[PDB]
Image (tube, rainbow over the protein chains, first blue to last red):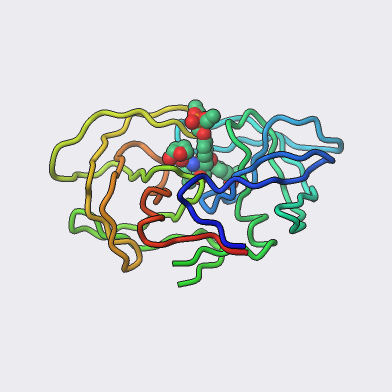
Length: 99
Length: 99
Ligand SMILES: CCOP(=O)(COc1ccc(C[C@H](NC(=O)O[C@H]2CO[C@H]3OCC[C@H]32)[C@H](O)CN(CC(C)C)S(=O)(=O)c2ccc([C@@H](C)O)cc2)cc1)OCC
């Protein structure tokens, strides 16, 4: 599909057996999701942007479905104010910017 | 152009007569640039990111050329970690997401 940018590019994702709304974010290197108790091992990480850094848990090889397009990669979980689909997964679903 | 996301979507912009590098950022509502000198009036504003809120200077109706496409809109100037082009200007240059 084609997503205009008049409004936030929010889409439905499926992760860890749950459906959620997330932002398709070309400004994010990697993917950051709201607090959720995923199974498996993880390692602590710090990610920063406007306003400073937050503490997150890094999970590797997590399967996410984004608008019916499957992707598998690293997912950071923590007190992010919004679910952010970053380039690590956007590339896997063939997402591009066009103007 | 069509821009893939294997690398950060960095482009050259022209603002206030100076060239800079900025990130096309579909997860940003607004455009925020690092500390710089711009002519004209401005008003204090607050903007919140993944880490919290920062103080910025709001410049309205600013001419900015993004990858050869002209825009005139609001530019926020403050301690952002990177120059980001937000949806307020991405819409002006006709940018969409496609997958
Ligand atoms: C309930 C809402 O809470 P808030 O309002 C903020 O919500 C948010 C917070 C963040 C975002 C996404 C970010 N956008 C953003 O900063 O946009 C600003 C400017 O325009 C405004 O629009 C939205 C906010 C304003 C951006 O796309 C991506 N970033 C990197 C850029 C900065 C280089 S990143 O997130 O920092 C990030 C850092 C490291 C990594 C690792 C993993 O690679 C992955 C992502 C969108 C909405 O207040 C909270 C106190």
